[PDB]
Image (cartoon, coloured by chain):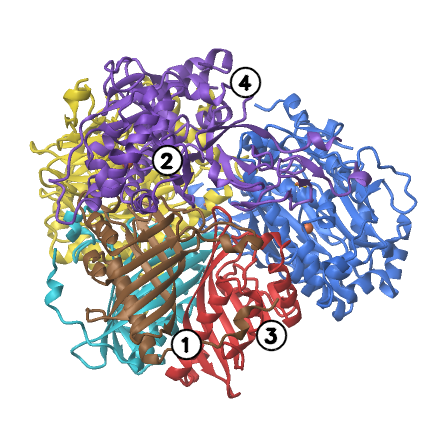
Chain colours: A red, B blue, C yellow, D purple, E cyan, F brown
């Protein structure tokens, strides 16, 4: 019962220096978010960022191509540099009630799998996360998923910029009242 | 036990008062499921969700799981997603195409119409299959929008909507080609009563005109501008339906509300040029100057809410007194330029999804509201719905029906009064318009 | 208040209709804890769980935690795991060996019989310790299985089981050596009503003979075989107890699903050779050809369920109308070869644990049934329990009792009819056999 | 419905018997919110939590969220944290300083007194603002502590407290400087009824003189010392208030409890030298030899609890029958040496926070009791409350009031008795002292 | 109180290269499971795999020896290569109702501790995990535990085969209705 | 808004060997706690340990400086070597009811960010965790947060001692009935 994957040879393994560099980048990025340093975080995002979190649905196996929303469909996020900017303005605003008082998040990053692209200093990265959101007195929202990034070497604080991010969230119906956090 | 008399005193549309128990009480909630959700026309989606023979959507009607399916003859059928054998879900995916439905428990098989057509071992172990299929709802379509109702004695949809139809038409009746749903339907959970949501879209521009959406507006205005430069819209009107508790409110000649939310390209589409002219010409019979209606909220009672200029559509599924699910999608004109379709898709995601710069703040309100109502004193004094009392009239030279000011709780007082009626009058003979 | 008239309306064994409310209503459940679980015989485990003086198991009778403890005189005692001082749990671990129990809260001390033998500062603050030990349950043993009953008025165990005993004996009475439990008791939680669980094991071979276990069977056959080569049986019978809600169903002469579930070494052990022939002789007094019974399910009302050829046993602990815990173990003949015992252990884990290739699909069904019952229209019509209506006879030449076909709901109707009786007849004078 | 006759039979102080349903029944709980929490004096914190004008604390009265705010005139107002327009939380942070409070939903604005002073679009849409502010509570102070009561016909604070005040003064009235709250208010959640917590601090020194805290003591004793050396305090007394349900118990002369819990520096400060002799002089009018009172617990009914020599204070917020929140802080004398304040801080963290070496074990008991009460038979018989029954006298030479032995349930019977009285006497005409 | 471990010398540290390889192995394994590449995941199992998940129980400290089910006792899993194969056959079956429609999982892997054994290219590995399973509309099951593996260098895609796996789950009673997932 | 962090230089990256060493120390620490080797874990604590978990509260953005409890306030923990000892004596006690029967915990560690201090062989480390705690029959308590440690190289089995630990929990109100676990 075989798959076309069988004819492909696995990618070049990321070297140790690079594996560490990219892990360290995500850890420092999670710190930014978990400390609410939103302007600092927004500075990581490339001007050509597409930040995309598609909808995920329950489908029978024989309709698996239909699991996620498409190119022209609604999504939970489908953002550009300019649309993210407005989000930053809202979340840092005194009159942004959803995040004033601020929520308390933890982004636990792991499973970082790195691939060198045809373009030097540009990398495709796949990683897993659990995002713990705690809000107000007793609200707890826990998210799990994977992130597919295109990262570029850059002369910012952290040494990389995020050129693309796709968030595949392990949910159909969102169990949270909102997505007032960044992934 | 809730007597008719007890229920009538939960609302007072005279003094403009609401009893806060209406949103927290379990008994009242169970009654709503029978008296409100059991016999109301509820929105299930759009004709475009199910265009082909066998195409299906699995959705809800209150807490009753239903399957919406397109028939060979082109009609849409709606039947309970429950096997009458032992209660199993017949249709087990979100959406897709079916040639039939088979129960996974004991393999009772159904056709795409919900007719029980095969019982394994029927000869050896058994009863008339034609009397043992899933309960069927009535199915009624308004210009794309698919509605459904369990109740045989309920008013037809057109009669149910009545004079609210011109306001729906602002969104739904603008092109000969009709609207279509953009792909995808978002689902999330807010711990609040459905009436906070259905009301807000029925009657409440007030929250968007005051403090709730100060930060969402900020997200949509240019980077060079801050909030002190923001145009505070004060001009507009509010419609209370003659019957049903339906409601719509909109801004008039103040595009700044629509610009920040939907951007220049959509704001132009809605107000100036061929499309907008055609739309005003098509809505001519109403006499309504729809090119001047720039930002609108609407609720068809109980749980069908939408935002006619941004074309965000949503169903509120009740989940007890203390929770709802919101199922959202978005409509575009089938013949709108691909530029304008894309503007609608992006800006609806940006503003109105779970992560949206408006949506975040609406639900933040409702959650804390529902939380306070767990208190004894929090429920002991009534709430104030006195805004715009006796200020509405049907004379209006621009907009038909019972029309008043954009900041008013008339549409609300109507919705709640219609909620109260359905909850105190058991017979459609007294209740119908 | 649920009147006896109203409760008697919930189940109709004549017409074969079940009111879906039985599985959902909170008030009926509170009544079940009193009228059913409060006075029925409930399975706690096996004698081999507590083989030595002081060995205990912490388990449940309904939602009451109890301690089952082996006494010095070799009897078994069952008391409420609750201190009569302020209600603390007396026995705080799952199982093990005790010389005494002591409450952690204020140090009331008990012997292994559950008798209060010390109260710290008795002379200074006090009352007869002999009157203040935890409530005791009636204890009784049927061929290794330990049952208990709170109610001093209830019929003794043998009378309560009645003509259900022969079908229990197929599993429990095959050797002079008796059965023994394999070590370990698996525990997991399913969001469903206990009656779905108990009914299925009571009466429902149908779900296994149709759709539910196509994939578990697939997992069991030779790798070289596919489903369209599998022999899913059609021959067998169903028993309904003369009294008490008990029921069993089994395949006759058709080893296919026994072979697929338990493999060839267990199947042969069960059907042919010395041990199988002894089993037939031991059950000779029943007149049953037990060697031709290959795949069987049983429930002893309310919540004691097992699968004789595979030797899987389950206790359903109720957790409201919307939840159960499943406590599962497996039995082997105490003198079975090490090989057979190991096949039993292996194949029980494979098929019937929480991760079992059969069990995954049993619970999958129940989860979705129960979610649907939150709906108003989902409870508004009766479920079909009409299978095998009128087709059952008492005078079958091979199998004793009221006997019908393997795909039938006679045992089901009997179980729901007795449930109904237990819920509406408050006194044993009318309820007893 | 619970008749007054039914409620009266839930507690029997004469026989010392308690109906376990009181801790589990949902109907009783809803009744409690009205008849108990809706008209009791409940602790909100200390005056030092809000020292300056505009300083606020968002806390609870029952399940009613309230704001406690310091006024310019140096009074303290407490009002419902709920906006009367549509129910929004007015004060959205835990604590801090406000110039005003504004509702985030529609923008109704309030001063620090809770008076509604602005409504956006009041002229265009509208009604007396002075009648649409959040509900106010009576506010009264006892030697630092802030209590509040919704019921205008309830006894003033001093009357409500009555003869319990000497035992509170042991902690609250030791110097002219008065107490101050150490900064910080820990909050945690326990799945148990509030009455177990209230009773324990009211009447239960027993749990601590027996088995619950053996390891808590072990944590605190010298490393070169094992539990067998640890001292067994057995000498002491217990007070049942004349009216109200209040209670306290304490050790006399035996400082092993105190020393292990609070260390040698707090012990010496409490019993020897200038501050100890000042405290005893200050409480001379009571006749109480307070320097000999070493380790003490107290509850001011319903839910104000504390521990005089360790100065740990708790409010129990009810969250249904099956859950509470614990809000905890500590008090020190305002002029206590820095050395002493720090010892109070450390040891309160060590022993009494959520991770406390004492607290871990208190909640372990309560979690399990509440779980057990899910059972039908667990609720079928009364709990024993007969300790020291008929042994308390009202003329003790050292301690004023109805006084018994340290290990007794007299205060406890009094707490449950006054609870029944509040639940079954709708009128302060009968209920008041 | 002292323990016999005090007479043991700490095990030799796994080098940087071997540490990263094994981590990457697990991340790629978790990818396979999370993307439902079941046939491909099964290929990582050595033919002599013992895949074991014992029952875990509440015992007093003086009976700690009794915390887990034994060799001859029931378990949640106790699998060979053969029985795992049937389980692959069921999970990839159109008529396997528990996983059609399929669940959405995330295996977050961390805490990877590597011990080289007496046989070169065979390793004992201890790791921690959180397994987030979201199913149908609103169902969320969260697991945590440790896995104790024996891995051999292999000539497959990922460079390692799984020779032995034991999963110690932090649960007594399983809070989930099934274990339709793989650990 | 611009922030004063803009004038700071990024920290000197921890070398790969040091990164691995510290990550492995945390994984072994987690294993000790998760296996209830309380005495062995206590051996990891420096005699000068200050072990602190401040309270955390909901504050408007404009009162952000008041989010956590202060130096002289109540806290969830605020421990020295001597006080931690007492806690170790309680948890290992047959009469320590909260942990007899013991709970079942998983300490998942990631995001390990290492800073070398002025003093050689002393390191500031910031890491993230999820702590999954399962108790008795059905209780599950999930914590998330970050840990701010100071580790010194030591001649113990694990190679480092914990000189300081501050735990920043993503909670205001504790959703657990206790903190009978260590962090
Ligand atoms: S429940 Fe559908 S066939 Fe039995
Ligand atoms: S509760 Fe058992 S001794 Fe007090
Ligand atoms: S809810 Fe307070 S202003 Fe509307
Ligand atoms: Fe809004
Ligand atoms: Fe089955
Ligand atoms: Fe205590």
Q: Determine which residue is flagged by label 3.
A: A49
Q: CA distance from mark 3 to mark 4?
A: 65 Å
Question: What SS does tag 2 mark?
Answer: loop
Mark number, residue D153: 4
Total count of labels: 4
Camera-side residue: B10 or D356? D356
Q: Is residue E123 visible?
A: yes
Residues behind callouts 1 and 2 on a single chain: no
Q: Determine which residue is flagged by label 2.
A: D192
Of tags 3 and 1, the one toward the viewer is: 3
Question: What SS does tag 3 mark?
Answer: strand
Sort mark 1 into few (<14), some (14-19) or many (20+) by Cα contacts within 10 Å: few
Q: Determine which residue is flagged by label 1.
A: A2
Q: CA distance from mark 3 to mark 1?
A: 36 Å
Sort mark 4 into few (<14), some (14-19) or many (20+) by Cα contacts within 10 Å: few
Residues behind callouts 1 and 4 on a single chain: no
Camera-side residue: A66 or E116? E116
Tell me the subunit letter for badge 2: D
Of tags 1 and 4, the one toward the viewer is: 4
Tell me the subunit letter for badge 4: D
In the figure, residue D9 lies in which quadrant?
A: top left
């Amino acid at each position: 019962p075989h798959f076309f994957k069988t004819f492909e040879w696995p990618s070049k393994a990321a070297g140790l220096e690079l594996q560490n560099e990219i892990e360290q980048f995500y850890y420092r990025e999670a710190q930014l978010l978990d400390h609410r340093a939103y302007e600092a975080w927004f500075a990581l995002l490339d001007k050509d960022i597409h930040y995309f979190m598609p909808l995920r649905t329950n489908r029978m196996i024989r309709e698996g191509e239909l699991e996620y929303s498409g190119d022209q469909d609604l999504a939970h996020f489908d953002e550009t540099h300019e649309t993210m900017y407005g989000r930053i303005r809202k979340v840092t605003s005194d009159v942004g009630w959803a995040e004033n008082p601020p929520s308390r998040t933890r982004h636990l990053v792991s499973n970082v799998i790195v691939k060198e692209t045809a373009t030097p200093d540009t990398f495709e990265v796949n990683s897993a996360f659990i995002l713990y959101r705690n809000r107000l007195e007793r609200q707890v929202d826990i998210f799990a998923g994977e992130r597919r990034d295109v990262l570029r070497r850059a002369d910012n604080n952290l040494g990389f910029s995020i050129a693309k991010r796709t968030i595949l969230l392990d949910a159909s119906t969102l169990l949270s009242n909102n997505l007032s956090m960044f992934f | 036990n809730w007597t008719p008399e007890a229920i009538r005193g939960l609302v007072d549309q005279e003094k403009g008062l609401l009893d806060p128990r209406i949103y927290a009480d379990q008994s009242l909630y169970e009654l709503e499921l029978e008296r409100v959700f059991g016999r109301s026309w509820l929105l299930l989606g759009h004709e475009s969700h199910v265009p082909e023979t066998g195409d299906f959507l699995a959705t809800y009607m209150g807490e009753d799981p239903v399957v919406m399916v397109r028939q060979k003859d082109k009609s849409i059928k709606v039947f309970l997603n429950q096997c009458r054998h032992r209660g199993m879900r017949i249709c087990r995916s979100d959406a897709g195409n079916a040639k039939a439905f088979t129960c996974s428990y004991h393999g009772w098989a159904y056709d795409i119409a919900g007719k029980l057509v095969n019982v394994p071992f029927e000869k050896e172990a058994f009863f008339d299959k034609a009397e043992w299929g899933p309960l069927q709802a009535r199915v009624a379509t308004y210009k794309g929008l698919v509605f459904a109702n369990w109740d045989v004695q309920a008013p037809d949809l057109e009669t149910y909507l009545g004079d609210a139809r011109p306001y729906m038409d602002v969104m739904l009746d603008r092109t000969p080609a009709g609207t279509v749903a953009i792909g995808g339907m978002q689902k999330w959970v807010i711990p609040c009563n459905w009436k906070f949501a259905a009301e807000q879209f029925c009657s409440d521009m007030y929250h968007a005109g005051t403090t709730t959406h100060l930060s969402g507006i900020l997200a949509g205005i240019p980077p060079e501008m801050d909030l002190s430069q923001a145009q505070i819209p004060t001009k507009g009107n509010q419609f209370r339906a003659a019957w049903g508790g339906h409601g719509s409110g909109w801004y008039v000649d103040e595009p700044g509300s629509l610009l920040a939310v939907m951007g220049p390209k959509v704001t132009q589409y809605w107000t100036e040029g061929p499309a907008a002219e055609l739309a005003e010409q098509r809505l001519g019979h109403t006499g309504m100057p729809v090119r001047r209606m720039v930002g609108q909220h609407m609720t068809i009672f109980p749980t069908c809410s939408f935002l006619p200029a941004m074309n965000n559509i949503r169903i509120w599924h009740p989940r007890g007194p203390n929770e709802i699910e919101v199922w959202a999608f978005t409509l575009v004109d089938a013949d709108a330029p691909a530029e304008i379709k894309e503007e609608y898709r992006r800006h609806n995601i940006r503003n109105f999804s779970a992560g949206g710069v408006f949506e975040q703040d609406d639900g933040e309100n409702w959650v804390e509201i529902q939380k306070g109502l767990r208190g004894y004193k929090a429920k002991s004094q009534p709430l104030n719905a006195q805004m715009g009392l006796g200020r509405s009239q049907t004379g209006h030279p621009d907009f038909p029906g019972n029309v008043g000011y954009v900041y008013a709780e008339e549409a609300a007082r109507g919705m709640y009064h219609h909620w109260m009626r359905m909850m105190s009058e058991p017979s459609w003979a007294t209740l119908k318009p």
